[PDB]
Amino acid sequence: SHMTFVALYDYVASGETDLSFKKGERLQIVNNTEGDWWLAHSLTTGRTGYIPSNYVAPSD
Image (cartoon, rainbow, N blue to C red; front, side, top):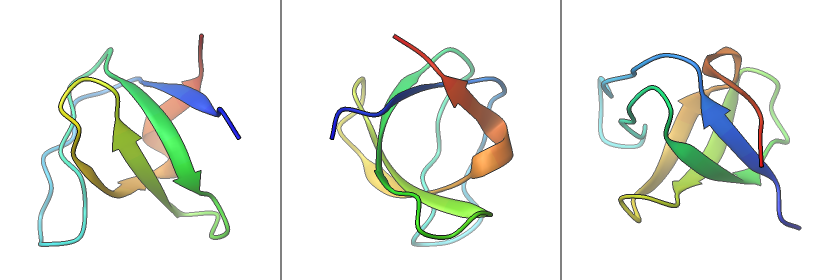
């Protein structure tokens, strides 16, 4: 259930459904059913949206 990942790079969202996040931000992964785009929730900003799965790595 707790699935914490850390952002490896900045990402500015290009649309409505993706999530913008800063390098070093910690995110709860909500839905990793797809291998390319994961639904994530920022523990910092409280925003929720899709992120590129290759921009994050497992974290505490």
